[PDB]
């Protein structure tokens, strides 16, 4: 309980910034995650023996895929840490505990394919879960790991606190289904602009946590350009494999996923920034002003994509 985690000076400082990259050293990621829980939640939230055993089982159940991997898990958890630390007083003890774990768990056992490819392939998980297929599986895998012996990091909570924190985690993980984001953001837009947004309304908190999750999940677009550009290779590597697998089912994939249409990428990024990323962080900055740096970074990268098209890089 007196055993703090410390980072090197550069990481100690950089980690507090939204645009922080967790680095190429896999063996430091678990200490980074624990450092973030201890500062975000307190050194008292989790039994360190249990948290460390949870972290390593969660790492184990991420696959070696180009993008939806252990590094993504921690990257997304760091973005939530930054949001939580810049909005200290707006979130309950349970929400701080639950959301960092939700982020670490949000993509558990991802295979590299969209809900859409699971449905066209007729994957057993598409029969077990008709909507938000991969996201119901991710939450399902989270509960499994929490239920391993020595892995219940919530064991010191009351029965009711426990049901609250698994409910926070379930909503949070489901909300990373980008299909649900559009509607969630429009409702939040309307509530903020007709002034009816109320953070004491549980149904309204749910929506705001949902948007935070979408924000953390898309935070690749909020890094400094060299990080954003290199992550896009990993993102597109998964997309083109899925495209290849669509072709194998005798279905032309959308151009985004067709590796014969690499030319179309920069325009596809534009569409994504304009349709998804900028709207996401605009609405998030309105509800949570201290998250503006995410919007500013996302804007800078939209501009960097415009320069790619114009042949200036
Ligand atoms: Cl740059 C970026 C980040 C996240 C995205 O959403 C995803 C959904 N599933 N895997 S990645 C993007 C989708 C298209 C183009 C760019 C994207
Ligand atoms: Mg996901
Ligand atoms: Zn994700």
Image (cartoon, rainbow, N blue to C red):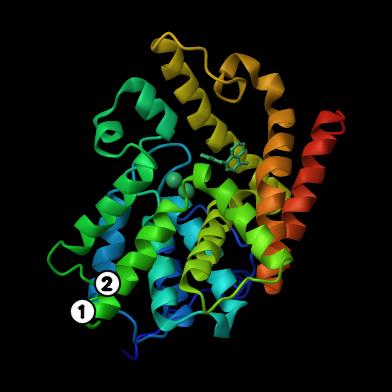
Residue 212 x %, y % = 55, 62
- Say if mark 1 contacts mark 2, CB within 8 Å: yes
> In the image, which disc is placed on residue 159?
1
Residue 43 x %, y % = 38, 85
Residue 114 vs 175, above or below: the answer is above
Residue 224 vs 161, above or below: the answer is above
* 162 with respect to 218 (left or right): left
Residue 169 x %, y % = 37, 63
Q: CA distance from mark 1 to mark 2?
A: 6 Å
Q: Nearer the viewer, residue 283 or 242?
A: 283
* 177 with respect to 265 (left or right): left
Residue 261 x %, y % = 64, 17
> In the image, which disc is placed on residue 163?
2
Is the residue marked by circle 2 packed among few (<14), some (14-19), or many (20+) residues within 10 Å?
A: few
Residue at the far bottom in the pictured view:
2
* Residue 128, image quadrant: top left
Tag 2 secondary structure: helix
Q: Nearer the viewer, residue 36 or 88?
A: 88
**Rendered residue at 31%/63% (across/down):** 55
**Rendered residue at 55%/49% (across/down):** 181
Residue 47 shows in this picture: no
Tag 1 secondary structure: helix
Quarter of the image where ligand 2 sits: top left
């Amino acid at each position: 309980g007196l055993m703090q985690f410390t980072l090197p000076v550069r990481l100690c400082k950089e980690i507090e910034l939204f645009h922080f990259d967790i680095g190429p050293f896999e063996n430091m990621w678990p200490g980074i995650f624990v450092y973030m829980v201890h500062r975000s939640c307190g050194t008292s939230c989790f039994e360190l023996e249990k948290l460390c055993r949870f972290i390593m089982s969660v790492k184990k159940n991420y696959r070696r895929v180009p993008y939806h991997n252990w590094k993504h898990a921690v990257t997304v958890a760091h973005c939530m840490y930054a949001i939580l630390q810049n909005n200290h007083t707006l979130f309950t003890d349970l929400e701080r505990k639950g959301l960092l774990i939700a982020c670490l768990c949000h993509d558990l056992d991802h295979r590299g394919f969209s809900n859409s490819y699971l449905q066209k392939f007729d994957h057993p998980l598409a029969a077990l879960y008709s909507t938000s297929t991969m996201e119901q599986h991710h939450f399902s895998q989270t509960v499994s790991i929490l239920q391993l012996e020595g892995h219940n990091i919530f064991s010191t909570l009351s029965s009711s606190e426990y049901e609250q924190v698994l409910e926070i985690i379930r909503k949070a993980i489901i909300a990373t289904d980008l299909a649900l984001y559009f509607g969630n953001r429009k409702q939040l837009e309307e509530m903020y602009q007709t002034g009816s947004l109320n953070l004491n309304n549980q149904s309204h908190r749910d929506r705001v946590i949902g948007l935070m999750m979408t924000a953390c999940d898309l935070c690749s677009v909020t890094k400094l350009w060299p990080v954003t550009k290199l992550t896009a290779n990993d993102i597109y590597a998964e997309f083109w494999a899925e495209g290849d697998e669509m072709k194998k089912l005798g279905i032309q994939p959308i151009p985004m996923m067709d590796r014969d249409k690499k030319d179309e990428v920069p325009q596809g990024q534009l569409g994504f920034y304009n349709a998804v990323a900028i709207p996401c962080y605009t609405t998030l900055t309105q509800i949570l002003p201290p998250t503006e740096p995410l919007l500013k970074a996302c804007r800078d990268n939209l501009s960097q994509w415009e320069k790619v098209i114009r042949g200036e890089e």
